[PDB]
Amino acid sequence: LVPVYIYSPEYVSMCDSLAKIPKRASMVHSLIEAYALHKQMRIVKPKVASMEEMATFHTDAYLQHLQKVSQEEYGLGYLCPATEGIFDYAAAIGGATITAAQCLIDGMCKVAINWSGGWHHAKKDEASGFCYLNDAVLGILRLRRKFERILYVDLDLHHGDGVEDAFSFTSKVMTVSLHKFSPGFFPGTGDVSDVGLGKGRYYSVNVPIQDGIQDEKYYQICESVLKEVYQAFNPKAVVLQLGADTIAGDPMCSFNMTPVGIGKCLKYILQWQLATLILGGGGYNLANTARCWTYLTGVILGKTLSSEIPDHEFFTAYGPDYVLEITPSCRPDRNEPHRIQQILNYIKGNLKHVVI
Ligand SMILES: CN(C)c1ccc(C(=O)NCCCCCCC(=O)NO)cc1
Ligand SMILES: [Co+2]
Ligand SMILES: [K+]
Ligand SMILES: [K+]
């Protein structure tokens, strides 16, 4: 049947509050609306995550803390300050991801979308990198009720450390993250020699990338890795994290990608035809993130979209040119193709240890 699109007016208003990405949620949805793609999807009201559902991953001590400070010392510092209503926004986004997982279980759909999810840094007892709750972990754990092996792919600019760590000692969930890996660059983990630990050894994969990667070399990397993971690990479902802080024009100022490069990655995964749970993440050039996740939504739906941005609530944000396409910046590509090749070999090596 048709892709699920998780959405409600109130969920969006809630996610709009998030101080680092104000009104992003409305922008993304408004743009998806303007292209009529919600017509071609099933809309499902997210449920709010209960206290017990969040404790499938997070500790009770953490969670009760989060709640208390939401009314008026678990990582709630500079990057995750303890503002009002944060407990509720966290529950909302957690429930939204879980809800999508549920839809995939009940075979309602083969793809389910929560663009406002993708909070990949949160730990069981600590906030991190703007992430107060790990919704990707919550959804993976929900998918494990039905699906034997889960692949978590993370294409955010940043290492999916929170999700990797949660599953670091298990062979039931494999984590693949492609990310900027550089001294000083958050969160600092996920060098190619990071493979997980114990029973989980070889069931974490990390691709370290330098500034200025563009669509071609990026897709070459991504395809090469996923092909191997697919053959070795033979996943029964995919949780996919598509943070748009990789996209040219983002103030993270790092990668030099366009949504076409990412959708080719998404297409690769989609052809496996598994239960796939699609998440957003970072993305701080707000119009650009909307263009990306709108385009990606086109891809999910095998639609080609018109190059001119329809008029809608946030049309002014798309000036001066009002086109869907993003132009690569002229920034240097810092990725030596030798280093990339050793990275790919090192991973191919690693993945030989994975036999199901
Ligand atoms: C005062 N000073 C010199 C500094 C203050 C903050 C940062 C920083 O960490 N910036 C990066 C914030 C991390 C965001 C990661 C969240 C994300 O998009 N994950 O996907 C650096 C220097
Ligand atoms: Co990010
Ligand atoms: K990543
Ligand atoms: K693992």
Image (cartoon, grey):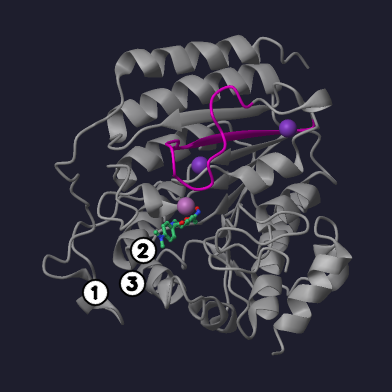
Q: Distance of mark 3 from mark 1, alpha carbons?
A: 14 Å
Q: Distance of mark 1 from mark 2, alpha carbons?
A: 10 Å
Indicate yes or no: mark 2 CB to ligand 2 under 8 Å: no
Q: Quadrant of residue 295?
A: bottom left
- Residue found 38% across the figure and 73% down from its top: 27
Instruction: Give residue 34's mark.
Output: 3
The residue wearing badge 2 is: 290
Q: Earlier in the sequence, mark 3 or mark 1?
A: 3
Q: Earlier in the sequence, mark 1 or mark 2?
A: 2
Examine the rendering and report whether any part of residue 46 can be seen.
no
Residue 128 in picture, x, y percent from top left: 61, 58
Q: Secondary structure at mark 3?
A: helix
The residue wearing badge 1 is: 317
Dot 2 amino acid type: Ala
Left or right of 287 on screen, residue 179: right
Q: Are marks 1 and 2 in contact (CB under 8 Å)?
A: yes
- Residue found 63% across the figure and 17% down from its top: 231
Left or right of 324 on screen, residue 220: right
Considering depth in this image, is 25 or 164 the residue closer to the camera? 164
Considering depth in this image, is 254 or 352 the residue closer to the camera? 254
Circle 2 packing at 10 Å, graded few (<14), some (14-19), many (20+), is many
- Where 78 sits versus 271, above or below? below
- Provide the residue span drawn in magenta: 172-194
